[PDB]
Image (cartoon, coloured by chain):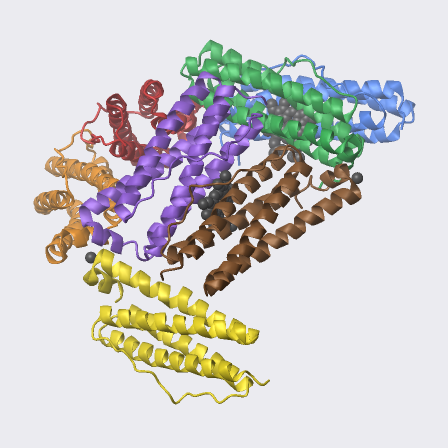
Chain colours: A purple, B brown, C green, D blue, E red, F orange, G yellow
Amino acid sequence: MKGHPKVVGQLNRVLTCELTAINQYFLHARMFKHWGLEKLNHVEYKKSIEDMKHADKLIERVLFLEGLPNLQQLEKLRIGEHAQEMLDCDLAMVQEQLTLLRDAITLCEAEQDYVSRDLLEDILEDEEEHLDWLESQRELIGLTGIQNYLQSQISES
Amino acid sequence: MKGHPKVVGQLNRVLTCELTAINQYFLHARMFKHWGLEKLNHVEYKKSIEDMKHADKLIERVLFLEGLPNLQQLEKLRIGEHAQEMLDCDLAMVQEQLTLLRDAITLCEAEQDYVSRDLLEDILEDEEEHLDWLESQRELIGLTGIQNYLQSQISES
Amino acid sequence: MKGHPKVVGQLNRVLTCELTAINQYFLHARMFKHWGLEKLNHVEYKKSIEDMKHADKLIERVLFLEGLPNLQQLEKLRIGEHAQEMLDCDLAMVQEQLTLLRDAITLCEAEQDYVSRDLLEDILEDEEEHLDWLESQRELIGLTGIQNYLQSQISES
Amino acid sequence: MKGHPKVVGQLNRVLTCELTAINQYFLHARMFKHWGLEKLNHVEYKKSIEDMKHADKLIERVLFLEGLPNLQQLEKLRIGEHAQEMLDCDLAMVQEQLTLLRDAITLCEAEQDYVSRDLLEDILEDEEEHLDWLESQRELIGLTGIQNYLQSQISES
Amino acid sequence: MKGDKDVIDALNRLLTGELSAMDQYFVHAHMYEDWGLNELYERIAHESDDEKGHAAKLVQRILFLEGVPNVAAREALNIGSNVEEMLRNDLAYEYKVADDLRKVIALCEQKKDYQTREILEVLLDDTESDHMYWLEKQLGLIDRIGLANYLQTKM
Amino acid sequence: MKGDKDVIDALNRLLTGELSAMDQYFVHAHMYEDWGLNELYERIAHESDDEKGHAAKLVQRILFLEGVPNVAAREALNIGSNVEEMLRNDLAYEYKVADDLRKVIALCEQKKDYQTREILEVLLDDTESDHMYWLEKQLGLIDRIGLANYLQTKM
Amino acid sequence: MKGDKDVIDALNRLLTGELSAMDQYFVHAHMYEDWGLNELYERIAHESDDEKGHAAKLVQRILFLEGVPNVAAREALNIGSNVEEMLRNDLAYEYKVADDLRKVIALCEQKKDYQTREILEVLLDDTESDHMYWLEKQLGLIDRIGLANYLQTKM
Ligand code: HEM
Ligand code: HEM
Ligand code: NA
Ligand code: NA
């Protein structure tokens, strides 16, 4: 089905941002593994796998809409040096990506692209569950301290 | 363990090339799925998963060697328009990446980095098994024709 | 719950079109079975079963909204003579029915009928997955030829 | 096998009537479900499934006989407002359809179309078992009253 | 995240509605059990549990949106005295909840708060396709078989 | 049976208490979940469910005694802002419920309503041996290991 | 077969290293157990067992190469007095073993003794990817959470 050019452009931009998220989440997961923080590894890895599924769905939607998926471009990665900075960078990226998703859902509704909108709404609920998790982690660092919080991440389960 | 700067640079370059391979293989797998060629989808997807594991191992090795994994850079993607062109682009990328791996193995041996060399040798055997598969596919297209070859890819198993 | 008259009219029109789709898909599935093309039989039959479920849901929604389901009217059936013509007729009907679904989703949103809209969005995603499949089949006929494509449909699995 | 034109015409007319029966039985089953009469739902739904199988067999027979199945035409639907009226409409349709089946069996015997006759005899035994069930329901309404009879249909099993 | 102020107010009104629904379904289920009508007791108790699930989802959403859930406020309960009256009160109250849910879904669409929109769409789907439909079926059955036959099936 | 009028009034006050407890434990459990403190969320949610069970028993007893359960009235909720405050509010409110339960058990003994006495004795046994004791243990643990260690165990 | 004389000498030095590692990991694991730090006890005991496996492989290779394994000689053990010191001594000694393994792998490559090369490459892969990495992670965790939090996780 020939999709709207604006919808394909928005999907390609959400795809760029999902790929940037995959890369940042995997680098952060492996930086966490390198420090022995295994539960943070596990969370960031499953989140990178999740954005992997999201990018897969966006590529398939851009292909179905007879567009050209743009896997070449990536955004700038925010790689932190320590756990708090990495969590803040992840938070900032989730927030930017949620703003982007909301703009794309608005445009998909304006163009009567309703299955693109359903796709983007699944991506939105997932990204906003991870936003919830990151805010929980920040509150936990504020509550128990960074040393106690990091001690809880040593064991993966 | 503090690794050699040359070995970390070579590992980062092999990592750039593994990430480029992941992106190209996934775009090609989903272009194949979009055309109903399901067995080609499956092969290109498992190959992208394999280069995914390779990039994971390279990131972990660069981190263990107290280097900075470079997930930001990607090489230029060769995306084909039809099956033969996509297979040729995959072939060209495997060949370039094998040359790179051989240079990196030589350097790792010259620096007595033997576990980096073992890592790169696993990546080499995998990449060169996929080279074998791509050459098999080209011979099969030459033997049965492109229409017969593509008909064999319709069903995934 | 007393539904909007416009929403019930749109649901009844989508129902007419879903019933026409059931009839056309079943006639085409049995024309395919008559020719020994068993995998095409299976696809067209499961698609007719799927539009059967869609018509069931539309009837239940029109009844819940205190409307009168119109199972009496059917649209004109496009019955092809050969496989390509039948697939093109199926494509044309899916495209018309998708346009209809999009108009109905727009109207359901304008009337704050949000569960009617959710129903129609499920029907839209299903119809547009079948649109994807039909476009895949057309690309496969263009790639492998009609004789090779039809040979792949002889065995159902 | 090239079938007799009269036999194919009779099979197409029995097919029109079987399709009309499918539609009427499904509308009635869902009207019963909408009223909470679940056992009546179940009976009318399995009867619509049964006429579905009958229409499938008639389509396959008309196709084997090198005829054109007519799924486009439907007869007028008798949709009742309440349970007794719906059961009477179902009764009237079964009786008309049984008369039609008997005429078609007579013609199939006159044309030495004996497998068409066996098909139509299976359809006849099924339709006349449902005639038996409908007459049983009318006798039960006369015996226990309509309020007691409808109370027995609330639970599906 | 920081939710829209109007979206949090509307979510809090929906929460008041769900909590009042819980109380009304609770007392009605137990009034049905006191009368030996165990099938209505079980159905209405499970609906009170579903209202508790909806209220949990709304409270979680209000807290995520950095609002203060209001579980103290309650709407006036309309308790029936006989089975038909309690079923009609439950239906009136489901109608009010569905209307208010539609208003808040429209508001969430205007305020770009899509995720609250799907939470409320799941709530509206339950309200319509789970218990408004059931109540309309029950009142239609009372109309068809009579109240004494209807109550006999509910024991 | 026809219950004593004072016993039904006291049962209705206990019902108001149990329903307010349910609301407070509900919002506190969800405030704990919003903060990532899943162990407190789960514990306090199960206690809200136990309050719902107690309220069900009280409503059943009031209806059996031919009274009218009052599920509309609610006491003022005391919602805390931080973990220690919410635990102390839950403890204060459990103390009040236990005191009021003891008064009503004494009343049921004077009014010869022995069966209401054992229903309320089971309620008092839960209130003391299930969650008042747990809250006192939690506050003592906060005193022993500190609040940051205590909250670390609750994730 | 008749192995190269230099390759057997280097294999015997690697054997002395592995045996000293075994002794040090043994006494350190038991010093961890004496202190109630059972997770460190178990980890360091399993590493002493892996050192025993490496020493077995080296002895088998030296005997196959028609050499005389030297299990009598031992390097000086560096026993720590507190957890950080024992972890740092284990890390220093893993570093020394990895350096010496690299020298012997280079020698086996020059002497065409490829099979000794892969035996030592498996040993080096264990030394790096099994316990040098683990020790660096442990020291980084001590740096991040502190020593008292780190030791609390090891009980
Ligand atoms: C830094 C780059 C990446 C790394 C290190 C990485 C790593 C991984 C790993 C380890 C897996 C699981 C493999 C398995 O256990 O079978 C995976 C799964 C997957 N990846 Fe990636 N990946 C990367 C980028 C991407 C990209 C860019 C895409 C698509 C555009 C992608 C698509 C997928 C898909 C579809 C899956 C399957 C989901 C699943 O595991 O269930 N990946 N990835
Ligand atoms: C030309 C008309 C139709 C034919 C020949 C037909 C045929 C069939 C057949 C053979 C089955 C599978 C039965 C079984 O194996 O148990 C089926 C299933 C079904 N049909 Fe139809 N059907 C027709 C129209 C309809 C219509 C108009 C509706 C609803 C408005 C409908 C609703 C259903 C449903 C709900 C199912 C169950 C889905 C399933 O099989 O899992 N059908 N149909
Ligand atoms: Na062929
Ligand atoms: Na601690």
**C90 vs D28, nearest the viewer:** C90
In this view of the protein, can residue G72 be seen by the observer?
yes
Residue B44 is left or right of residue F89, and the answer is: right
**A10 vs B69, nearest the viewer:** B69
Please name the residue shown 52% across and 17% down the image: C102
- Quarter of the N terminus of chain F within the rendering: top left
Residue D14 is left or right of residue G56, and the answer is: right
Residue E34 position, x and y percent, is 29, 35
Is residue B25 placed above or below G134 in the rendered structure? above
Please name the residue shown 17% across and 45% down the image: F116
Is residue F129 placed above or below A24 in the rendered structure? below
Farthest residue toward the top? C5
Residue D29 is left or right of residue A146, and the answer is: right
In this view of the protein, can residue E37 be seen by the observer?
no
Residue G151 is left or right of residue E143, and the answer is: left
Residue C78 position, x and y percent, is 71, 17
Residue D87 position, x and y percent, is 60, 20
- How many numbered marks does the figure carry? 0
Please name the residue shown 14% across and 51% down the image: F147
Residue F145 position, x and y percent, is 14, 57
Residue F137, quarter of the rendered image: bottom left
**F155 vs D27, nearest the viewer:** F155
Please name the residue shown 35% across and 85% down the image: G74
